[PDB]
Amino acid sequence: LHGLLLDQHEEFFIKSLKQFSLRVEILPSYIPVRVAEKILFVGESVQMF
Amino acid sequence: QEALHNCSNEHYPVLLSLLKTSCEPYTRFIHDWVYSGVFRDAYGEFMIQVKLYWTHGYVVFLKHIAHDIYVCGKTINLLKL
Amino acid sequence: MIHELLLALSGYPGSIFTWNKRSGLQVSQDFPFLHPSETSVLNRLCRLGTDYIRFTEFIEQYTGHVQQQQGQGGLHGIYLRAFCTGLDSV
Amino acid sequence: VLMKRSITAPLAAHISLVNKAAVDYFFVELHLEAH
Image (cartoon, rainbow over all chains, first blue to last red; front, side):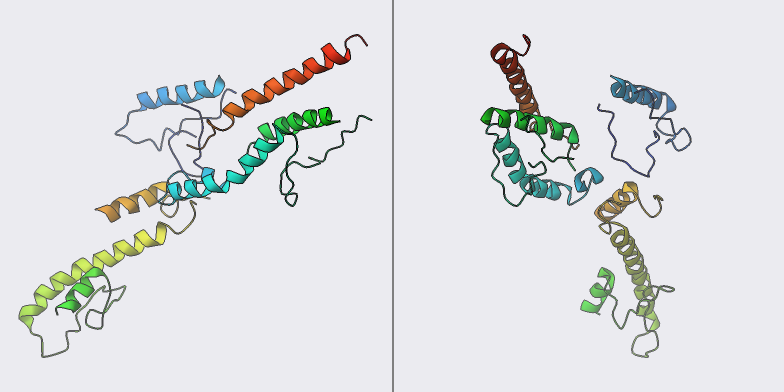
C-alpha cells in the first residue's frame, strides 16, 4: 500500500521506475508465481505515483 | 531509528510507548517556534538555532520538514524586527 | 524422585540427571539402590527433558539476543525469531 | 508501520498559510513589485 520496506538483508521474494526485482528462486511453492507478479506490479505502481 | 529498525518484537509496543513520551518535549518545541517565533532555549538542544540580517546557523527525523520549519520561523522573526 | 524428576523434566539438570551435550540427561546408573525395572521408565522420561533443553537453548540463543538484527537466515533474520516464538508457544 | 499521519498533517497545512501571508505582506504593503 505504500511501497515502503523495513526489511534489510533478508529475503521476501521481492528485492521512480524500478527498485524492485523479482526473487523468483526463493519464492514459496505453495504461493503461486502469478499473484506475486501482481504484487510486484502494485508495489512499483504505488512507488511511481 | 530503533523504531524503523524494528518491525515486530515483544518490546515493539513497549518501545512505541517509550518513544511516544520521549518525543513529548520536542513536539512542544516545534509548537513554540511556529506560533510564537521564540523558543525557550534550554541548552541549545533544539536542532535549529540562531541590514538583511539573516545569518542563522543551521548547516534522525525527516529533514524534509526541518528546512520548512527553518524558513517558517525566520520569517516571523523578521516581523519581530 | 518426587521433586528431582520434575526438576529434571523442567530443564534444570541435577546430580542424578547429569547434563552432557553428547548424551543429554542421563541417570547415574551405578547404584544397586535402583534396579532395571524403574531404570527403563526413567530413560524414557529422560528423552523429553533432553529435547526440551535443546529447544529452550535455541529459542533463548536467537530470540531476544539482538535489538532486531550481513544476514543469514539460519542465524539471523526475523523469520528464525518468529519460528522460535511459535516453537515456544507450542 | 512507522509514519506520521496525525502530527505533520495538521502542521504542514499551517506552515503554508503562514508563508502565503508573508508573501502577501511583502507585495501589497511594502510595494516590492513596484520597485
